[PDB]
Length: 217
Length: 216
Ligand SMILES: Cc1cc2nc3c(=O)[nH]c(=O)nc-3n(C[C@H](O)[C@H](O)[C@H](O)COP(=O)(O)O)c2cc1C
Ligand SMILES: Cc1cc2nc3c(=O)[nH]c(=O)nc-3n(C[C@H](O)[C@H](O)[C@H](O)COP(=O)(O)O)c2cc1C
Image 1 (cartoon, rainbow over the protein chains, first blue to last red):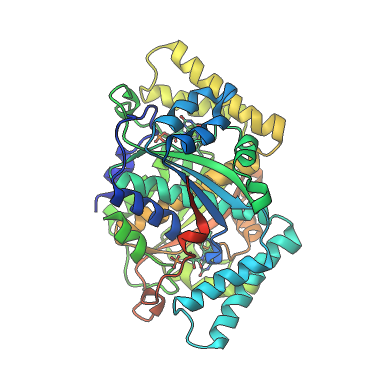
Image 2: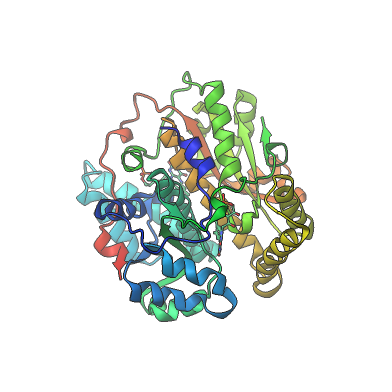
């Protein structure tokens, strides 16, 4: 697969064609990509809101009013809009949920194997939630890893997307009652097909030279 | 078929030290690191790419104490990437990014460049002046790069594993990162898994979508 060509062709969509929708199969693949991203210890400390109705997208778009109005149209016009959310705390129940799911999927040959996995994950989680008091940051980082996986994955599907931090995430959290549910919103990714007006699709891609960013040893 | 790639890649537990990347694959690895997106194209990152035994040994110093279980992966993989974030978003870096965008022909006019610079500075100021979280903001962009990278190398047919289980203070000291304005965050060995790594064969486990996805 020519993934480098995918990486060089994908770009941050500036306008979506509001008439072009994902197929049913594409929508399923989108959710599979969200689900199957890796994460530290397979902790999966995340929730996703996938908005595909006009009202659902309008609820997300409420967070882009005023200061962030330049991002509001992207949210309204795309086919499917993903709100990436992190857990606000790594609680005991979630750690148990993850390891129980690994058992349900047949990853452990014995109780001892499950216990070793649980102990190892709990060690890392405790380092963050007890020692460093940064489990919120640790989990948010895993969500961003998922975003990076997602942007390349949808590009490889032939879909356009744009990662969006330019919204009011406090408004978004309130609109979707996220804090009470144990989550906080971090990134919005509209997905679809760019419009004929979006000339960012052809503008040269710009990055700092490797002589600046890469040291080879 | 990127979904098949996503379902086949896995966290490699042991690498075959005899299986090196080709020269072309090594170039593609660096292209993937360079061309990841980031908020405002801020690219707030540096990468150490170790491909010699001496270079991998420097990285492996961090896989000590509790983290010895990750030492072999770092030594045995063909190429090992240390992902680093800037620790502060300074004016000079913002100017460097926008000057590079001009050099690449993204702006029709000085006015267009000025608008781009103003918009990026607005976001940077929100983090570095208002929220005082620019370090966290930049680290998040590095993790986005990691996620792009893991899927990209998988699509190239390469094995990899993201590693947080090392002592990043040792890694920072070894590479003098803090005084240069950087901190190391993730180590990703890349290569081909050992035939003895049966984690390649075990079922992939994730929470059901009924738990993690709300459709609206
Ligand atoms: C986390 C993140 C947030 C971003 N926020 C926005 C945004 O709010 N609106 C927007 O139009 N583009 C946004 N961008 C797109 C970036 O400007 C873009 O990724 C960068 O300029 C690199 O160019 P490319 O994505 O076209 O390769 C965001 C990108 C990332 C990764
Ligand atoms: C940021 C990050 C850090 C990780 N740390 C380690 C590590 O130190 N050592 C390791 O063997 N695996 C590590 N893992 C691998 C995870 O356990 C793995 O991604 C998770 O179990 C999901 O399964 P999969 O990657 O096989 O699909 C890490 C993964 C991520 C994303």
